[PDB]
Amino acid sequence: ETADLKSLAKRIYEAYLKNFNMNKVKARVILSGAASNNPPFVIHDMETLCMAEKTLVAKLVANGIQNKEAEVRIFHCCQCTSVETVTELTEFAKAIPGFANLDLNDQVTLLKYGVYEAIFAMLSSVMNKDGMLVAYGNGFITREFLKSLRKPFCDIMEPKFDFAMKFNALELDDSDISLFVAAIICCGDRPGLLNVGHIEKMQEGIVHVLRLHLQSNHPDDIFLFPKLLQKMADLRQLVTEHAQLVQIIKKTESDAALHPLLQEIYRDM
Amino acid sequence: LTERHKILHRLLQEG
Ligand SMILES: CCCO/N=C(\C)[C@@H](Cc1ccc(OCc2nc(-c3ccccc3)oc2C)cc1)C(=O)O
């Protein structure tokens, strides 16, 4: 790698560590249990959900979901985490050299279509075959408990776990993920992009740094880059399917209210 | 116009 190409790697990685509260290194330490014997409170049933909620009481009441169905209460808590991640993602994007310079319209489009791809890409870091971290690493909701919920709420996460399990097998660290996320954000393939040409160029540089980083970070996984290239397509479809389900949930659920910020994201997607 | 993304837009501007 060259100087110019290096500063890009370093600048993106720092933005990642700075803007995202949870990251794979902290997550693996919690899911491993090698640095502490105080594991996350496990949420595996309604009983344990209600208990965990006693701590989230202030929040739930604040948004008036205290008495909503357990699925809707969960659906909503998941939205808040999404709204929070979109906020960090926006700051992270503004940190990628060349992003802030883009027409404000293209900035919106990029975040609009990339946010969820990045979200599920990053959510894998806190997922394993039995469940996933919640509430900043303090809780652990089981994969089984999620499939126990009633339809359609139980058809939301299972597909993500399936993806995460294959993605997690790639053994990427936070240095790989930062570049990977920046790439999914600066995608010249988005619908309605004004300056596809320039953005495509920006995407090339980032993609270039990614390719070279992967080679010197994972010398034994020769085709890891193209593998990640496939993962990018998989995430695209994954999110498309996710948008579909959320659409079904909206037109068929009285209390499935959608947070505004998220609302504008799904609109026309 | 694509500014039917007011909240997101504001995040892009202020923070
Ligand atoms: C099950 C429906 C998913 O819907 N996803 C949603 C609306 C979210 C995405 C999302 C964000 C974060 C997630 O994982 C973290 C998490 N946090 C909890 C949690 C549960 C109870 C209390 C506090 C937190 O459960 C889970 C899995 C899953 C999905 C959306 O479509 O915007």
Image (cartoon, rainbow, N blue to C red):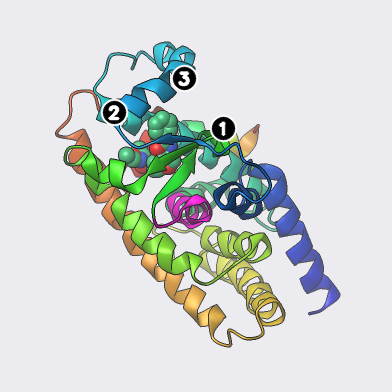
Verify whether residue A124 appears in magenta: yes
Q: Read off the residue under disc 1.
A: B10
Q: Read off the residue under disc 3.
A: A56
Q: Residue A175: x percent and y percent? A: 68, 63
Above or below residue A202? Residue A50 is above
Between residues A266 and A121, which one lies in front from this camera angle? Answer: A121
In the current view of this chain or complex, which residue is farthest to the right?
Answer: A3
Q: Locate residue A215: give its quadrant.
A: bottom right
Whether label 1 lies within 8 Å of ligand 1 gets the answer no
Q: Residue at x 63, y 78 (%)?
A: A211
Between residues A143 and A267, which one lies in front from this camera angle? Answer: A143
Label 1 – label 3 distance at C-alpha: 28 Å
**Disc 2, disc 1: CB below 8 Å?**
no
Element carrying mark 2: helix
Q: Amino acid at mark 3?
A: Leu
User: Crowding near pointer 3: few (<14 within 10 Å), some, many (20+)?
Assistant: some
Q: Read off the residue under disc 2.
A: A46
Verify whether residue A139 appears in magenta: no
Whether label 3 lies within 8 Å of ligand 1 gets the answer yes
Q: Locate residue A164: give its quadrant.
A: bottom left
Element carrying mark 1: helix
Whether label 2 lies within 8 Å of ligand 1 gets the answer no
The part of the chain drawn in magenta is A116-129
Q: Residue at x 16, y 41 (%)?
A: A151
Q: Residue A206: x percent and y percent? A: 64, 69
Q: Chain of mark 1?
A: B
Above or below residue A139? Residue A59 is above
Q: Which quarter of the rendered image does ligand 1 occupy?
A: top left
Q: Amino acid at mark 1?
A: Arg
Element carrying mark 3: helix
